[PDB]
Structure formats: C-alpha cells, structure tokens
Image (tube, coloured by chain):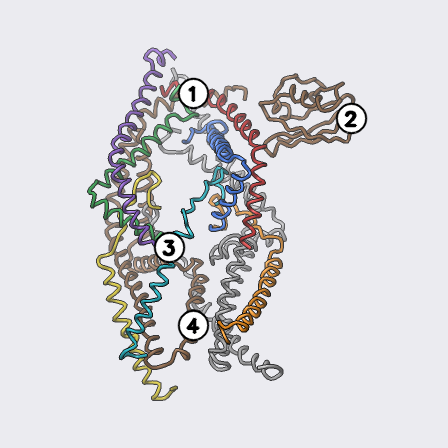
Chain colours: B orange, D cyan, E yellow, F brown, G red, H blue, I green, J purple
Amino acid sequence: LVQQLYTTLCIEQHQLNKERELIERLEDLKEQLAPLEKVRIEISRKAEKRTTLVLWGGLAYMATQFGILARLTWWEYSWDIMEPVTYFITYGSAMAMYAYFVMTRQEYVYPEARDRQYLLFFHKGAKKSRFDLEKYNQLKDAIAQAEMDLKRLRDPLQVH
Amino acid sequence: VIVTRSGAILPKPVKMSFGLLRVFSIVIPFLYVGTLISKNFAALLEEHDIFVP
Amino acid sequence: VIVTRSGAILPKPVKMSFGLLRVFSIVIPFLYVGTLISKNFAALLEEHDIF
Amino acid sequence: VIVTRSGAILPKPVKMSFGLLRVFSIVIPFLYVGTLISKNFAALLEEHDIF
Amino acid sequence: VIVTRSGAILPKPVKMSFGLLRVFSIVIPFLYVGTLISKNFAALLEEHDIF
Amino acid sequence: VTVVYQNGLPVISVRLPSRRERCQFTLKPISDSVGVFLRQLQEEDRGIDRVAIYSPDGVRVAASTGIDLLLLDDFKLVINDLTYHVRPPKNAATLNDVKTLVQQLYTTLCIEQHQLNKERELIERLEDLKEQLAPLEKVRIEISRKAEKRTTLVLWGGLAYMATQFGILARLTWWEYSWDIMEPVTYFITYGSAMAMYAYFVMTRQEYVYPEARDRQYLLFFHKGAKKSRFDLEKYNQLKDAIAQAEMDLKRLRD
Amino acid sequence: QQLYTTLCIEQHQLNKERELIERLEDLKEQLAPLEKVRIEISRKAEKRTTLVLW
Amino acid sequence: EARDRQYLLFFHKGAKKSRFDLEKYNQLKDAIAQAEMDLKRLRDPLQVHLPLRQ
Amino acid sequence: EARDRQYLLFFHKGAKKSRFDLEKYNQLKDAIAQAEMDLKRLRDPLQVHLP
Amino acid sequence: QQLYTTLCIEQHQLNKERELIERLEDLKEQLAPLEKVRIEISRKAEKRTTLVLW
C-alpha cells in the first residue's frame, strides 16, 4: 500500500522539491551576505593593520628599553648604578603585567592580548565605518545552521 | 579565537570605565605609602640597635 | 598535535615571509635609538643638573 | 569559570584542611635544617679550600 | 585530566629509555666545552684586548 | 500601551483611566489566559466597566483564549472608555505535512535493507581506500621519521646550548672574570631571551611554549622534508579523511 | 515498531513540544524570585572579591 | 583562574551566611537548560522535518 | 599537569604491583559509560521507545 | 496498529530495555571487584604523589 501510496503521491518529486527549497533558501542567505561581507573583510584588514602595528610597536619598546640600559650600564654609568633600576623595571613589568589582568580580567598572554586588541581595534574600528556588525554575526549563524541541515539531509545513509 | 566556529565575530570586550586612570591613581597612593613606611621604618632602626646603616 | 583526529597531517604552517628580516630590521634601529638616547640624555642630564 | 554552562553556580571549591598549618609544618622545620646544613657546611669548608 | 570522561584510567605515560642519562650525558660534555670555548677566548683577549 | 515578551515573558505596562499608573503586566505565554489576566487587571484598580479585548474587527475575543494567540496578532484592548491599539512583536495539519509522513514510512521500509547494502559497500570503499593508501602511508612513515630525527636532534641542540651557555658563564665569572663585571652581561642575556622569545611570537602568532614550538617546527621539518622527496601530502591526507569519514559512518551504523 | 514509531511521533513531538514550552516557562518564572536574592549575593561577593583583586 | 576560586568562596560563604539556598537554585537552573536544550532538539523534526539527533 | 604525569606513573607501577588487570577495568569501564549512554539514549523523552 | 498489538510490541520494547538494564547491572557487578582494588591503589599511588608533592 505505502508503495502504491508512494508513487501515487509524486512523493519523490515532493522530496526533491523539499530539499530544492532549502538549498535555494541557503542561496538567499548567501546573497544578503555578499554586500556586507566585503565591508567587514575590509574592516578586518584595517583592524588587522592597526593590530599588527602594536605588535611591532610593542617590540620596538622592548628593543629600545634594552638599547637604553645597554649604554647607560656599560659605558656611561656603572652596572652597580643601573642594576637597582633594572630590577625595578622587571618588577615594573610584573606589576603592569598584573595591572592588565585587573583591567582586562583575562591573563596577559601574547596571543590572547593580540586577540583582545585586534578585537577592540575592530568594534571601535568598525562602528566608525558603521557596517552593522549585528547583521553579520546573526546572519552567519543562520547560514551555518541552515547549511548544516542540508548535510543532515543529504546524509548518504539516510535515504533521501 | 577572534571569531567563533560559525564564522560570526566575538562581541566587544569590556574595559572598566576608564580603568587606566583609575588603577594609575590606586598604585600611586599605595606607592607613596611605600616611600613613607620605608623612610619611617629605616629611621625606626636608628633609635634601636638592630640595624645601624 | 601534528595530526588531525582523523589522521590528516596538518597543513604547513605559515612562516611570515622574511619576517625574520623584519624583526632583524626593527630590533637594530630602535636599539640604536636607545643607544644614542642613553648617553646623550644622561649627558644632557649631568651638565645642566645633578649627576 | 564562575558558573557552569547551565548557568548553575559551581560547587564550593575544596580548601585543604589546616592549609596554612599543613604547609608551615614542612617549610618552617625545613628552613632551619636548610639553615644548619649550610653553617655545618661552611665549618666543613672552613678548612683548606677556596674561602 | 587523569581519567577519561567515561571514568576510565589513562594509559601509562611514556618515559624515554634511560633518557635521564641521555640528557645528563649531553649537558655535561657541553657544559665542559662552554668552559673550553671561554678559556681560549679568555686568552685571545690578551692577544689584542681587554683585561 | 506597550508589549514586551523579549525577557522571556510578555509584560504589558498599561495606563489606567484617571491614573498616571502605567502599571506593568507580566504574564506567561500559554499557562495564562486573557481571563485571569483581566482578573489580574481589574483587581488592582477600577477600570472595570470594560475589561474587554476586541480583535481588530471589534470582535470580542474569547474570555479564555490563549495569551500567546492573543499577542500573536494586533488587537484593541479596551478599558471603561478608551482603547490601546497594541501591535505586539512577532499548526493545522495539512496535505503538505502528510506527504512527509508517507516518506518517513517509505524510508522505514527501505532503510531496513538499504543499510545492509551500504555496509557491505562501505567496507569495500573503505577496503579499496586502505589498499589505495598503504603505499602512501609507507613513505609517509619514513619522511615523518626523517623529520622526527631532524627535529628530535634540535631539542638536544636546543638543550646543549643551554649547557654551553651555563658553561661559558662559569669560566667568565669564577675562574677568569669577576661577578661584578659579568652580572650585567648575563642580565641582557635573560632580557635577550625574554625579548627574542617574544619576537618569535610576532613571527608566527603562535606563543612560544615548548610543546607547541616543537611541533610548529616538526611540521616545517616534515613538509619541507616531504615536499623535497616528491611524496604527495594532499592526496595522502585526502585519503586519510575519507578512510576516517568512511570509518565513522560504519561505526555510526551499529543499529 | 519502527513503522508505528513514525505514525505516533509527529503527534507526540508537538504534544511534548507545547508541554516543555510551559514547564520551562513555569521553571523560569519560579526562578525570578530566587535569582534576585542570589544576584545580590554575587554583587556582594563580587564587590568583596573585586576588593582583594585591587 | 585564582580570582574565580576566590570568588566562589566569597559567594558560598556569602550565601551560606545569608541563609539563601543554593542547592535548589542550580538544580532549578539545571532543569531549565536541560529542558531548554531539548527545545533546541525539537527544532529539527518540527521546523525542518529532519530526523531528531540525540 | 606535571603532577598528574607523575601520578599515573605511580599508578601503573602500583597497578603492576597489586597485579590487578588495568586494561580490564579500563575496558569494562568503557562499556558502562557506553551501555548506560545507550539506555539514556533509549529512554529519550522525545522519541517513543518506552510508553 | 493491529500489527503493533497483534504481537505485543510494547511488551517486547519494555523487554528490550529491561534486557539493557541487566546488562548494565551485569557489568556494574564485575566492576565492584575491580573497583575496590583500584580504589585502593588510586589511594596508595596517590598517597605517594602527595608526598613527593610536599
């Protein structure tokens, strides 16, 4: 019966039509994304240049603070004059490297710091361009989930 | 871990109300107690005999 | 962690193109700034005021 | 990690009984044995050595 | 971290074959050359240099 | 007046007659109904004459319809005299739904045998790939070892360094030189590392930690080692996905 | 069984669905008083613990 | 991390002092999410008519 | 971590000492957290397997 | 519907589940011996790692 019911109800046609609707709806979600995609993927680049600068700019500090205490120590003063500073600078760091934990509330670790920075150079660095991030993240959730259904549908083990 | 796995962008992190100019004015007072309770304590070993210099 | 849970070998990770020569070209000059600013500051310090 | 994924509040973290005391019982009586085996060593090195 | 999520116990973590010697016999002979490289260096400096 | 079911529950702050009391009205979506909602309304004030709720057509809605079904659409709540046009914010069985059911039946007749075919097919595709992969894997084993040795003889070459430094700063502190003319140059070392260690992080965005920074050099020692020997890597791992992709399925087919 | 499992489920879902959507609501409502006396303990313990962090 | 473990102590010592229950609060908060997550499971067979995952 | 990698090495050593098969307990413990999960997956309060 | 009750399916489903319980209660039995001797060692081998820790 169900087989007679099967063929007599153009079910496979409906079955295809079912998925065919979904894959189309996915394209719609893709279409809404393409315009607001480029403005973000640019803002990322801009917010990346500004955060790949701080990294370099951070190094230059830790390469001149060594350059300062070099000449001072060796041939402008005595090491026994500079030393009681260059312990403080160390402790000065291990104070800020804790102050950062008070402000940020996540431990200062070079990647996660670079993460939080590039993140902050983005939000601030995007609102100035005013590209409505709220559309992006929300939409990127659906297009992910919506697509994931198509996989869940076309599963080679479930007959569809 | 800037972006989530879906492809969305993580939210804006939260600084704490110009905290830089707040912490910077909580270290210094508790730093000035340092240059205070040090001088005070150093002289406090002059009137006694534990440490001469 | 060299292998995926599947068994695939991870892609050849990115080596910043000539980044070795990037850092090698920023740790030198800013040091030379720290060099020239070391002496020529304490100099301009001990002359006008205390040692 | 204050609250778990369900929003529930994590259990009370398990402090150790007599924590400050269970540790002083081993650092304090060892600072001193770490003290004497130096003094007894200097007086073991006081003889022909490099001072 | 010591037990799997299923409650099972983790496998025997690996100890390399007598590796304590493998490192102990690779620190000393290179701790010893650090001496030697300095000594000949500490002499080269009186050929044309400091102290 | 207002309508807010965004905090999880509808809340309806409404202005009562002869009152500035824009009093809130929280209410569940389904476990409550316009009946006790209006009971909750008329008890706290004297807007009693018309405790009524008119559908947009003026049709007086039921006294026990579903709260959600009410706020599912516009309507005209009314009091003794005045109305508050509320535009709130945004199931019958059908032939279209019935077809899905006939499918779930048909697939329940076919999936009985279809799996037994997929299984006795999956094994072979698995088996065919396993033999398709064995030569690739064989060379992969060696090149990895050619990278294994090349990197496991950098770790020692990383360690013995830390000896030949601790060996070059002994002689320059006790035997020959002072400790007052050495302490400086052995501090810049510690500050050379703690800055070059950092500069490595700029170079790879992969924080310098011994486990990671070993592997991120193991891979480099593998690809460069493999890319030279002409042994493919893409097609190899490509198979490794399928030979796992085809695997998880058969594992998933233990029903 | 698997056959009949199809005829009964699609109805059983909606019945179950429109059942959870209220006991969830029931719980979440029952929570509203209990969380406030909690959310003060936090803003008390938090203030007490954002003290030591300073 | 060490902040949060300290926070927890200030919390429980703050709650246990304030006599406010906690063993029910989380159990409630559990029953919500557990029930809530099931709603997310029913999204597949209802809105999408796709087999339920488990 | 380093505590644990020591801890297990105390375990597998002692497990060999008191001689009781670890893999058995390891194996057996797996099926429990699998058979049970299978049951929790069978009483699924959304499917219909137990009326 | 007839096939569902002509051969008491829900009597067999509940059997299948009941067969699962005993299997769980079969393993959970075999665990009880192995558990003790492991609870012992995982105490002893832990009593050492807290010593070396100290």
Q: Tell which subunit mark 2 falls on.
A: F
Say which of F240 and J34 sits in front: J34
Foreground mark, 1 or 3, reads: 3
Farthest residue, direction bottom: E47
Q: Chain of mark 4?
A: F
Pair 4/3: label in front: 3
| Numbered disc total | 4
The mark found on residue F102 in the picture is 1
Q: Quadrant of the N terminus of chain F?
A: top right
- The span from disc 1 to disc 2 (Cα, nearest Å) is 57 Å
Q: Which residue is mark 3?
A: D25
Residue H43 in view here: no
Q: Secondary structure at mark 2?
A: loop
Q: Earlier in the sequence, mark 4 or mark 2?
A: 2
Provide the residue designation for mark 2: F17
Q: Is residue J20 left or right of residue H34?
A: left
* Helix, strand or loop for disc 3: helix
Label pair 4/2, CB-CB below 8 angstroms = no
User: Between residues F191 and D27, which one lies in front from this camera angle?
Assistant: D27
Along the viewing direction, whichever of J11 and F55 lies nearer the viewer = J11
- Quarter residue F142 falls in: bottom left
Q: CA distance from mark 3 to mark 2?
A: 76 Å
